[PDB]
Length: 212
Length: 197
Ligand SMILES: [C-]#[N+]C1CCCCC1
Ligand SMILES: [Fe+3]
Ligand SMILES: [Mg+2]
Ligand SMILES: [Mg+2]
Ligand SMILES: [Mg+2]
Ligand SMILES: [Mg+2]
Image: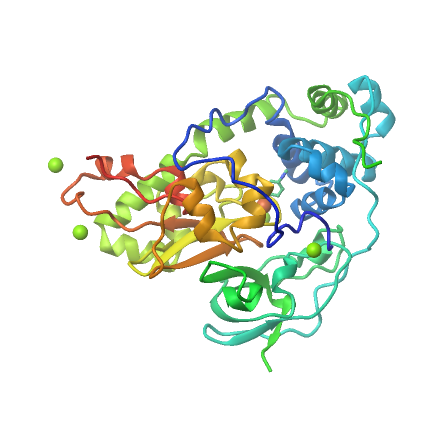
């Protein structure tokens, strides 16, 4: 999904609000902040109501301006609440009643997702690959800066996981794929307009094709 | 008009979500409290620091950490949520590694701790992939032109830690002494371990 959450390479932001080894304070800065993660795990592990991938996607589905003005932990309160409603566990009415006011949620999905790709290639370390020139309106674990770009495999995972584009929509056809550490030259991604060296993106097999 | 939607206070919404679920018997006794404990006390960069100090003094473990990070971390019992498949990345005299999740916040929680606010910022998420030298400089870390910067974008299930170079002036230090200078920011890759004057 080409949402505003796909921030890598966006220009115009100011300084990162940190200097190295500065005091970051306690893990949680407010008494509610542990709730999003804890209730996400309740949803995933206890209720079996949704996957972790569905949590990433529902946050991607926040209305874009809403996403941009919402603090991190609050995005997950909104996302987890949205999933609880979508999965029929809770109603928005009862959330708003308990909250004592408006509790707007993420927007409905505009894609049913897609299955794990039928035809993929097992790549080897050192092999040149291109990121498939594909557009996916639902969940995808490919930041746009690498779409269509060429890099070299530095690692093939020894484990396999469900394809995010499927499990992020709760589909039954996510299968399993390894992922690949794909090293791109900075210039491949940003031409002259970068001060970096290389960027390594961890890409599912189904996002890749042989180069040339 | 680009205005924010009307919303109840965030605390009220967060606790409403808790109460809605808890009131239906869907949240086990002490469940969220237990997670809060784990997040605050168990998931810690002190664990990553311990792994680095071990690697610095034990060539065999260093090699294990760099080839099968998961197995190395498992020896300490430090695998966990958001830290089940671990890859450690080695800084060298010509290479500096830095970790981000440009798409949200992905971080090796059990060994680095939950990500700090700055790591989750739009500023870091947008900028470090494209201009890591300038970002690190602004953050207080100068990386010379003859060092390649490599940014690992945590886009799948690999969970990363940086193994920084062992600084001069630490020869013969104990593991405890070495651990002390490996900070959270060193594990993320934005800082280099510092030796006192
Ligand atoms: C809740 N939540 C975020 C925690 C880490 C995995 C992706 C989703
Ligand atoms: Fe993330
Ligand atoms: Mg985009
Ligand atoms: Mg699992
Ligand atoms: Mg030495
Ligand atoms: Mg001594």
